[PDB]
Each structure stands twice: as structure tokens, then as C-alpha cells.
Image (spheres, rainbow, N blue to C red):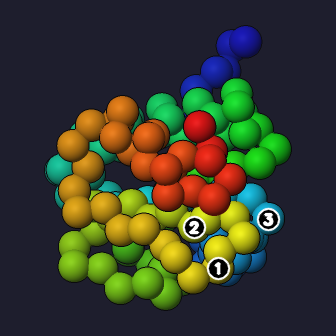
Amino acid sequence: GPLGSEGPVTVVVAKNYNEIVLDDTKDVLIEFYAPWCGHCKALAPKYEELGALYAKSEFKDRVVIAKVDATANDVPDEIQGFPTIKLYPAGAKGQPVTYSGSRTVEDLIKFIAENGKYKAA
């Protein structure tokens, strides 16, 4: 009620980065960004919306969309910059998709269900 915002997306830190992305029993969506980057700010509200969208509405107990920062944490995966979007298909621990630049939200959603093994959408 009084507090509806705050903590909208799932949090993934080096302390639980592996346990999460590893979870093949469910759909995982990790997005890396920088707290100083501007382009990331615009993608912040977008990725945050769709995140909680299915995270609780459709795949409440099947999908997990979290966002990590390149400042300090696990992030074993390499990055050219940051504005990155990876999707781990449930059951396929070796087929993470890599976005070449988010253009819209409709594309990010259709991707999770397209590349995602669980079809989180």
C-alpha cells in the first residue's frame, strides 16, 4: 500500500550471482549496467518494468529477472561496455543470448520467450 515502489527487480550480487544464473530449473534474465552511464538510465525503467511484470504476474515462481552492476561483483561474463542483456534458458546451461543493443521493450520481452527454454512470457 504505502510503499509500492523500491526493490522492483531481483537483486543479483557476487554472493548469489552463481546460484542464480546457475538455476537452470527456471528462466534467468541478467542485465548489466553502470551507475554512471546515461544510456543505462533510460534502459533502467524499461528493464525494471518487464522485470517485475512476469517476475510476479506470469512466471512468479518460474522466472527470475535481476540486474547487476559492472562496478563490483561476480559478473564472470565479459562485456564490451555494459548495456548488456543475457538470457539463460531453463535446462540449457550453455546457450546464453547476447543483445546487440536494446531498441524497445516489446523486443526484450519477445526475446525472453523466444530464446528462453521456459518461454518466460
102 versus 36 height, above or below: above
Name the residue beneath numbered marker 2.
Answer: 88
Residue positioned 54% across, 46% down in the render? 113
How far apart, in angstroms, are the residues tagged by discs 2 and 1? 7 Å
- 106 or 53: nearer the viewer: 106
Binning the other alpha carbons within 10 Å of mark 1 as few (below 14), some (14 to 19) or many (20 upward) gives few
Where disc 2 sits, the SS reads strand
Task: Give coordinates of residue 25: x percent, y percent.
Answer: 79, 65
Name the residue beneath numbered marker 3.
Answer: 25
Task: Give coordinates of residue 6: x percent, y percent.
Answer: 58, 34
Where disc 3 sits, the SS reads loop
- 72 or 17: nearer the viewer: 17
| Tag 2 near tag 1, CB within 8 Å | yes
16 versus 45 height, above or below: below
In the image, 33: left or right of 77? left
- 4 or 56: nearer the viewer: 56
Q: Amino acid at mark 2?
A: Tyr
Mark found first going from the N terminus, 2 or 1: 2
7 versus 2 height, above or below: below
Mark found first going from the N terminus, 1 or 3: 3
Residue positioned 22% across, 79% down in the render? 80
Disc number at residue 93?
1
